[PDB]
Image: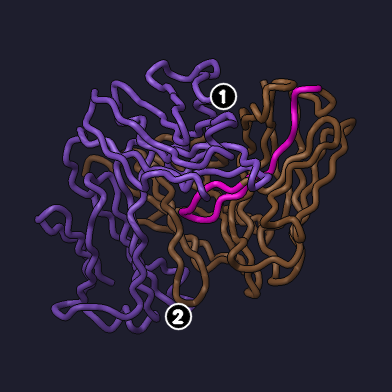
Chain colours: A brown, B purple
Amino acid sequence: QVTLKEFGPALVKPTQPLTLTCSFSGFSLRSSDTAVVWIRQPPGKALEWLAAIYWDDVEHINPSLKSRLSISKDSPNSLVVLTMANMDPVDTATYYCGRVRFVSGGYYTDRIDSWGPGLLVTVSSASTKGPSVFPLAPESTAALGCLVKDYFPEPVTVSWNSGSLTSGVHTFPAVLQSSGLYSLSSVVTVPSSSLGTQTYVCNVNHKPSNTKVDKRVEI
Amino acid sequence: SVLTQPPSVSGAPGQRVTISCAGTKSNIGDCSVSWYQQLPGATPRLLIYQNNNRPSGVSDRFSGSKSGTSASLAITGLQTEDEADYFCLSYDTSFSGWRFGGGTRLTVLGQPKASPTVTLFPPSSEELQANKATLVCLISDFYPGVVKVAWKADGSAVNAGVETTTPSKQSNNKYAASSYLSLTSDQWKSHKSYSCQVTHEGSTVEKTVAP
């Protein structure tokens, strides 16, 4: 069983450097058949191989980004670090961490068989803003919700009753206003009869602004 | 992205589809190809590695051949749950680096038509204290994934202050979307009633609120 986790900033100013850190578990970078790779994916476009560093310090870096990219590792601490110099808006993307496995010899038999959850990096001159959380309330069932209004940059997570309530939760993709601010909404469909007794709290997280707000949603 | 993929491939349930990956001898001709699946809004998953090999867990309905300067991923017994984006991967010696294909979106057709279940929320009182008013129109569970949203305030139409998201595939392969009408508290209090109108496959469906 193998897991990876990306660490990095949600927001980076133009021309500033991006530094990404991968922290893995369940395998060793000292293993003669493994490597760690960084993949990025811009919104609605193809996957892109950035860089990978191998057990024997072999580096496969994208030659289109060589002047901007550098990679380094720490096998005894299971850490891999990527730096990308001079960031542009165009470099706004989700960045993935992955274990490459391969056969010794074989001739480029490498494959990405494990992926981190990916980290969304936004390259903007705009400043971080936290959202304002608002309740959404009004015969069989009823729809309750929370408005997460005006935040930047992505992402935002929403749970209900600290995650004890998952059934019938639907959190919608965010809208991008002309203000350069994001907004989304999270509804939960609960039995009409339960409105009298059950108490519903949406948990709103926005790590880029270190914002975490609880909100009671009644009538 | 020298590796060429068809932008879109469609299929009816049960049939077999093919997703090609064309390149040069430098990349696909000599080196090994790997295939990657990406369910909508999810993390990529290894499907095929070394041209034709499956990892554990990966369905036997998937398979990869390589012949000449082009590679292919074949999917038999097509199911709705195969709706994803598919990327090939290979090393290129002339390029001296790894390159992906542009990717291929797979759509499966056999799904039942589903009308939108539209939900409209008024401004919260908390927001009205801030002299602001946001009308939230949430649209979900509709197939096909194409709708149109229009805002009516009383009789007249509304244009300004409307922001509508693109349709997005849910987990159940149905589609969801959202629309926001951003008003000041007094804009909201001035009219008699606001309406969100979702048009989907001919029939328009309406939801309406008021102070």
Chain of the residue under the numbered disc 1 shown in the image: B
| Image depth: mark 1 or mark 2 in front | 1
Q: Nearer the viewer, residue B139 or A123?
A: A123
Q: Which mark is residue A60?
A: none
Residue at image point 44% right, 40% down: B22
Nearer to us in this view, B185 or B13: B13
What x and y, as percent, mark residue A103?
70, 21
The reply to whether callout 1 and callout 2 are in contact (CB within 8 Å) is no
Would you place residue B193 above or below residue A114 in this image?
Answer: below
- Residue A161 x/y as whole percent: 53, 42
Residue A2 visible in the displayed image = no
Left or right side of A126 for B192: left
- Mark 1 vs 2, N-terminal side: 1
Give the quarter of the image for residue A192. top left
Please give the residue where the numbered disc 1 appears in the rendered image. B50
Horizontally, is A31 left or right of A102 in the view?
Answer: right
In the displayed structure image, the side of residue B178 where residue A73 appears, left or right: right
Say which element carries label 2. loop
Q: Which residues are magenta?
A: A32-48
Q: Nearer the viewer, residue A48 or B169?
A: A48
Quarter where residue B19 is shown: top left
Judge left or right: residue A136 versus residue A46: left
B85 above or below B182? above
Amino acid type at circle 1 is Gln
> Disc 2 marks which residue?
B131
Local SS, label 1: loop
At label 2, counting other C-alpha atoms closer than 10 Å, the crowd grade (few under 14, some 14-19, many 20 or more) is some
| Cα distance in 3D space between marks 1 and 2 | 61 Å
Residue occupying the point 50% across, 55% down? A43
B106 over B187 or under it: above or below: above
